[PDB]
Amino acid sequence: GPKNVSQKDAEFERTYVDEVNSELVNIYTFNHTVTRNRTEGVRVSVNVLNKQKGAPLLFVVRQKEAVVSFQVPLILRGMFQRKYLYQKVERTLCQPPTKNESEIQFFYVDVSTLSPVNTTYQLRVSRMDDFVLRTGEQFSFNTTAAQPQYFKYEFPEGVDSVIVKVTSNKAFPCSVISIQDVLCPVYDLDNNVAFIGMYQTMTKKAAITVQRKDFPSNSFYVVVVVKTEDQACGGSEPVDQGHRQKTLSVLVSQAVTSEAYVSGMLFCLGIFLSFYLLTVLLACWENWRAVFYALPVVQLVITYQTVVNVTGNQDICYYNFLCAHPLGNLSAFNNILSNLGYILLGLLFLLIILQREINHNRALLRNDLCALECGIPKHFGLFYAMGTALMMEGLLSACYHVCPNYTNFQFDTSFMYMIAGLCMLKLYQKRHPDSAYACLAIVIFFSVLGVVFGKGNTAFWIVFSIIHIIATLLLSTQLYYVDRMVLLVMGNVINWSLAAYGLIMRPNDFASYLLAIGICNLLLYFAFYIIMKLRSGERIKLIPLLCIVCTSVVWGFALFFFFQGLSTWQKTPAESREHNRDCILLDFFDDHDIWHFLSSIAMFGSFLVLLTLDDDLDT
Amino acid sequence: GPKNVSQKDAEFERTYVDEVNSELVNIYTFNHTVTRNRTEGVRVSVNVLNKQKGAPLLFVVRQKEAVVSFQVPLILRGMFQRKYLYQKVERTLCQPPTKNESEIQFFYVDVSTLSPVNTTYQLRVSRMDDFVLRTGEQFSFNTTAAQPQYFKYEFPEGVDSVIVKVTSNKAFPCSVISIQDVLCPVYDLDNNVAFIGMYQTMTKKAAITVQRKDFPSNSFYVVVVVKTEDQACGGSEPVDQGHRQKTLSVLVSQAVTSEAYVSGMLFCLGIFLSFYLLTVLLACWENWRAVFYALPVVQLVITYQTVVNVTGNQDICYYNFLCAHPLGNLSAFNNILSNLGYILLGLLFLLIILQREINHNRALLRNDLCALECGIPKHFGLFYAMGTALMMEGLLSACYHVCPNYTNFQFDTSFMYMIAGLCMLKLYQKRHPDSAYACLAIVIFFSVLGVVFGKGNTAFWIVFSIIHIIATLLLSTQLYYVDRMVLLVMGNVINWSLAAYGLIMRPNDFASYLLAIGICNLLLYFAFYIIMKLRSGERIKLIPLLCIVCTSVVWGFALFFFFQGLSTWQKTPAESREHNRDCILLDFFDDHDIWHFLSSIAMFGSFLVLLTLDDDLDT
Ligand SMILES: *[C@@H]1O[C@H](CO)[C@@H](O[C@@H]2O[C@H](CO)[C@@H](O)[C@H](O)[C@H]2NC(C)=O)[C@H](O)[C@H]1NC(C)=O
Ligand SMILES: *[C@@H]1O[C@H](CO)[C@@H](O[C@@H]2O[C@H](CO)[C@@H](O)[C@H](O)[C@H]2NC(C)=O)[C@H](O)[C@H]1NC(C)=O
Ligand SMILES: *[C@@H]1O[C@H](CO)[C@@H](O[C@@H]2O[C@H](CO)[C@@H](O)[C@H](O)[C@H]2NC(C)=O)[C@H](O)[C@H]1NC(C)=O
Ligand SMILES: *[C@@H]1O[C@H](CO)[C@@H](O[C@@H]2O[C@H](CO)[C@@H](O)[C@H](O)[C@H]2NC(C)=O)[C@H](O)[C@H]1NC(C)=O
Ligand SMILES: *[C@@H]1O[C@H](CO)[C@@H](O)[C@H](O)[C@H]1NC(C)=O
Ligand SMILES: *[C@@H]1O[C@H](CO)[C@@H](O)[C@H](O)[C@H]1NC(C)=O
Ligand SMILES: *[C@@H]1O[C@H](CO)[C@@H](O)[C@H](O)[C@H]1NC(C)=O
Ligand SMILES: *[C@@H]1O[C@H](CO)[C@@H](O)[C@H](O)[C@H]1NC(C)=O
Ligand SMILES: *[C@@H]1O[C@H](CO)[C@@H](O)[C@H](O)[C@H]1NC(C)=O
Ligand SMILES: *[C@@H]1O[C@H](CO)[C@@H](O)[C@H](O)[C@H]1NC(C)=O
Ligand SMILES: [Zn+2]
Ligand SMILES: [Zn+2]
């Protein structure tokens, strides 16, 4: 007649080799017994042998309630009208749940083409024996840009959230890992995948935190889809592309139940309400025996945070996805407690100055002669800024850590130098009792130029490297005697030891690097201040000296953890996600959160250097 | 046998009514003669009559080089697992260009289902006689969420850019208008549409500017896709949804060729190099006859601008899409020249102060007695700020107008009050020659609270309304005699006339509204300053008075155009795009760009009030 329609009764796990004309159509009738409980996923797999350029095979999979139709050799899209041609196509068949416990279910495969030559294909329908994922058990597979895959997970009895971790041992097939509910169809194509769910482009690691209140089915599909071009991960006639494949590994493990939150917050209070206990008991017994930054920052952040929450495109906020414990609508709630050190110490510092000035004033009322002529003259208008600034660093970082990003970046660390600036100002306002804000603004502007060029050319880096060493020998002679020539020994080597470290690494983060120059230069001056006392008639009581060794150590651990993550921020969040790590402390905090703890203790303990350093000069 | 396969030879523009079992499949063989030049688009259309709940029809359209397969009644997705069921499906068939001038082309339709009851459908394949769009000719059609449509445009001989304008007379089907190249397939589904191209959610208006350098085919497809739920436009068992349809209208018109740019830029220079000409000729003949805002602003903007340029999601930047002439990578280049008034007048102002102070200093060298005791004492450290501030308002608005948005919003107008503040400070520093920055920061913070609540509840508005009238009677008695009680007459009514206007409209924009309070309150004080002179022995020369009438008028036109668009910024850029308008002046500038022109002339002409107002007090 017009055409030829052949109706074979097909079988699972067998390979059929056949031929189709422009005048022949093949229909295969597969059938499987589905069970309500032990769902198994069917998976079709076709492969056209030595196809010419004439006309594709057209494959239709007809279930009871869905039609899925593709054409082999599949042709996929590049950026600039580039085409890729895959000879081998695979697809898992979505199928909805059943009201009966077990029932027989049919589906048909229809193979046809409109080319006048006998095309030979290779059809094999095989059942998946590893569909449903199990909690805490690794699993490996393969996928290409023509053969997307997806697996099922269903939450156990009494697990309210999991974290789907997917890893790969190599870089450049670029996968997308979407997470979708269990209602057919499954959006596992390059165009479909971004439609719904909450995805994550991966290169070596992806981690998605899932909570079963969003899934009334108590289950979800994990969908892995490779991409034709690697531009979104930092890479560089149809072009056959079947030679490019990706091996992966998926592990689903339960998240922290509820105690890591309670035992995490009872750790911040336990070591900062400890200082309040300590100083009060130390002071009591012994004695008688800015807004211009608050406004623009926050309202951008609230706008930016909800975007992912309402879109599920997790390439926006540069969290540490392996340790990011959500609470409410906050996706990294453990990076916000970490900023309790500033809010609880920058305030405690102010209380110290209050009573210090209040205790002082009574001496004038007592008509003390010392208060008028003995000791360095009082100036507590700068201490009230250091105490104020610290409290404002734990508020512009708690707002940065709601979506860390290239845009949001300057908010925290730029204000950090201000704190370091006041320490530099106070020492110079001490010895020479008779401005720098431009330099802090310049540094921010330089970091802004270092923000417009953070991944800037290495030519820019050596420009900064050269300029820094010029400013190294410039400020060297500003404060310049055997002891004086001792200064330039370390004052120039340490800066060399840092600028050189820049070229060896070229951290994509810049402002955070300048912070390293900040302390590493400043911390030297403290010694330069102390060596003045030791090599003169000046002395040190045990109260200030004790606050010198301790704070010189907490600046050691802090600068260690501040270095544990320094390159853990790159372009293309897919690359920046390769560096995430599990939670070190209490399984709630990681390296960075330790830095927010140690920095606030390093700084507060260096304020109480200045406060009591020149307190032996009273008499 | 196993099934029944019927092979009909079908015909165009006829309606076939047939039945299918779980044991019958229909195959229709359509054929059309395609021509290289006059491409016509085929369009299938199926409709299932009184379908039960059992099992869908499955439709496959098999061309020579593509398979398109759906299932009727189509089921579409809501937000929270809501399903919608369409009984009627339509689709235009994509088909690639032909190497022959004209050739016969076949395609098959396959109708089959797996339900055991005779389902009756209604298949009609009809050719489209209005496929290819023509330049400058309106065109109307219809579409639903099951029947997406797309049309073709190909650029004429010598037209380098067009603007696709689509309008609708009603609001709430939410369409998406993508623009894609002419390579099959066409992504005209809810999931596909966002994949590639450059789309725009519409409610009443959409306008996409297209440039044929991005399309080597010299043509593109305009794709219209309705949406099931109206949430993205501000709205509120499967639920049958075929009763909801959208009528549209598409007009493609050529953009400004090249002269609107040259004749636009030769308009900014012609009226600001005019002032330089004017004042120099007026002065010469007659006489002898901050950085803390530059850094955070810009680098966010460059990051934000390229996102649309690399994604084509034009619901991000709140341009005026009907008048937005691109140049380079800037999408609204006519909103950036408009800010040449500040850069060219805030600088000219400084030149005035220079020679004013330079001419002054020689009087002291000449040992003039007047310069020491006659006239109000000189203080040009505040004028050098007003001249500096103006130049910095035409730089934080030229950076805002690269993507206007809720986040980017505060950059320009917040700094505007600073300029108004110095004018208020100068007058009070004049009469009382012996701070407000907190109020400007508070206003920004209040506008920040008005930014966190811009669309805030009307309860918030009346709070501001009540508080403003309290501050109306508060500052009234600060500066308080028949003339003194004249002050409170207008000083309180005008503020009432504004706060009341707020409740009648409740503009979603807030900071811009506060600007209206800014001038409308400030502008009254100028009169309050002038009425002091007129009702005393004080006088006015013709040089200052001339600069009073003129600047009181340019504050009339400016506040007119500043009101022509005040609600033209809402939530959901689909709604905010209903308010766009064509270009008024030179077909390059619109209402807002006139405001950037008149504001800079209104301000500069009010500085030269203060400069020369009290210049009759010399002797
Ligand atoms: C369902 O498919 C199976 C194939 O897996 C069919 O079972 C075959 O039946 C034939 C005829 O008796 C025998 O070769 C075997 O019993 C089966 N073949 C196998 C297991 O390879 C079965 O007929 C199909 N069901 C229906 C209703 O057609
Ligand atoms: C993924 O693909 C790789 C091939 O790239 C598979 O590795 C092959 O299969 C087994 C397992 O090692 C060996 O017998 C072959 O020699 C392997 N080939 C190579 C080149 O290594 C791997 O098994 C696949 N992963 C699966 C099936 O889970
Ligand atoms: C292409 O389709 C057309 C239908 O539009 C077929 O033309 C029909 O041919 C029959 C047989 O002679 C006659 O009824 C008319 O000539 C046509 N019917 C119409 C116009 O309604 C034509 O046969 C098809 N071509 C092929 C090769 O099958
Ligand atoms: C879009 O649909 C409307 C119906 O909602 C069509 O209007 C109908 O068709 C013609 C044109 O006015 C009239 O004879 C009918 O009475 C109209 N019905 C109603 C209720 O107004 C309109 O024609 C369609 N647009 C097209 C086909 O371009
Ligand atoms: C296939 O078509 C040919 C026509 O040449 C003829 O043998 C018959 O119609 C069909 N036979 C089979 C086995 O399909
Ligand atoms: C199982 O499914 C069949 C349809 O194949 C249906 O007729 C039957 O009612 C179902 N079982 C029960 C217990 O309802
Ligand atoms: C293959 O093509 C030949 C034409 O040479 C034709 O006779 C034959 O029927 C086709 N199919 C097979 C299975 O040989
Ligand atoms: C349809 O199937 C029936 C079987 O009951 C039989 O008439 C024949 O096989 C087929 N007839 C037609 C016209 O398709
Ligand atoms: C027109 O198309 C046919 C295929 O149907 C092809 O054989 C022929 O070569 C084409 N015409 C020319 C001039 O190449
Ligand atoms: C409709 O269903 C009946 C069963 O009652 C069956 O006999 C018949 O073949 C079906 N088709 C038509 C066209 O009547
Ligand atoms: Zn931090
Ligand atoms: Zn503006």
Image (spheres, coloured by chain):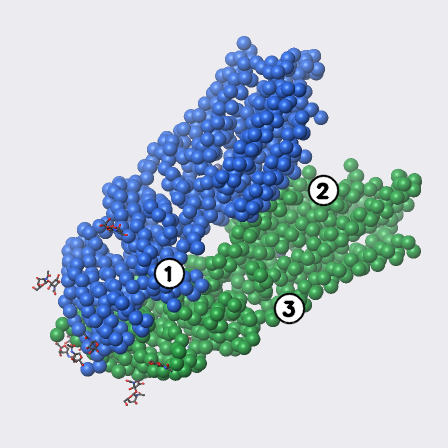
Chain colours: A green, B blue
Quarter of the C terminus of chain A within the rendering: top right
Quarter-of-image position of residue A239: bottom left
Q: Disc 1 marks which amino acid?
A: Asn
Residue A74 x %, y %:
31, 66
Please tell me whether residue B285 is drawn above or below residue B195 in the rendered image.
above
Q: CA distance from mark 3 to mark 1?
A: 39 Å
Disc 1 target residue: B191
* Residue located beneath label 2 in the image: A477
Left or right: residue A399 versus residue B118 is right
Q: Chain of mark 1?
A: B
Q: Identify the chain of the residue marked 3, using the numbered disc in the image.
A: A
What residue is at 66 percent from the left and 53 percent from the top?
A394
Q: Nearer the viewer, residue A525 or B112?
A: B112
Q: CA distance from mark 2 to mark 3?
A: 52 Å
Q: Chain of mark 2?
A: A
The residue tagged with tag 1: helix, strand or loop?
loop
Q: Which mark is residue A260?
A: 3
